[PDB]
Amino acid sequence: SKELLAEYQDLTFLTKQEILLAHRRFCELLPQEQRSVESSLRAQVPFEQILSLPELKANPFKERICRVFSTSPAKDSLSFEDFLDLLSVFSDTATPDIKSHYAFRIFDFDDDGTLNREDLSRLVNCLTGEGEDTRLSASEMKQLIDNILEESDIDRDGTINLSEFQHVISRSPDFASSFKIVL
Ligand SMILES: [Ca+2]
Ligand SMILES: [Ca+2]
Ligand SMILES: [Ca+2]
């Protein structure tokens, strides 16, 4: 199931939490004997259930919306992938972020899903001491890593996951230029 859901993460640039929330909603819109993770990811939700979606309530052309997001020309339904895109457009519970996705993968050296002290050390090391061309000392690197955890490691597990990473660089507009965190 982890590998299966992970595929969608690479396809949409959403966090695992976002995909999980969406998957639960998707399943609840399918037929009872369809909830099976691997089974559900192959099912399609009929427009009936999409039209009554809360985030589409105030939208005119709901019928049009369904047809545009639907990938299968034959059927009048949405696949899980189509559903993710719908939520990315109409719901605050799904916000694609291609920059966070790749930046995270770059610093997650062992590709294990989180940024630990070691991964974070390279991240903060992209910054400078004080002058325009400086390099951090051990203690400065330590403090910077400590500050990131203290401020963004909200599930207090000692690492930074994609969701938390998005918060770490949420105030760094030019982050991708040289991977510098603001402050
Ligand atoms: Ca959205
Ligand atoms: Ca890691
Ligand atoms: Ca964490």
Image (cartoon, rainbow, N blue to C red):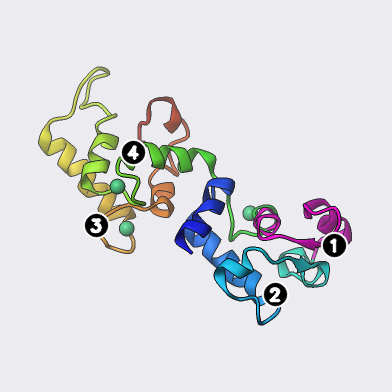
Q: Which secondary structure lies at badge 2?
A: loop
Magenta highlight on residue 76:
yes
- Residue 20 vs residue 52: left or right? left
* Residue ID at (24%, 17%): 133
> Residue drawn 34% across and 61% down?
154
Q: How much space separates mark 1 and mark 4, taking CA atoms?
A: 41 Å
Disc 3 residue: CB within 8 Å of ligand 3: yes
Task: Examine the structure image and report whether residue 166 is included in the region drawn in magenta.
Answer: no
Is residue 60 in view?
A: no
Which residue is denoted by mark 2 in the rendering? 30
Kind of residue indicated by mark 1: Asp
Badge 4 residue CB within 8 Å of ligand 2: yes
Circle 3 crowding by C-alpha within 10 Å: few under 14, some 14–19, many from 20: some
Amino acid marked by disc 3 = Gly
Residue position marked by numbered label 3 in the rendering = 158
Which is more foreground, mark 3 or mark 2? 2
Q: What span is colored magenta in the figure?
A: 58-86
* Residue 107, disc: 4
For the residues carrying marks 4 and 2, which lies nearer the camera in this image? 2
Upstream in sequence: badge 4 or badge 2? 2
As rendered, which of 65 and 90 lies closer to the eye?
65
The outermost residue toward the top is: 133
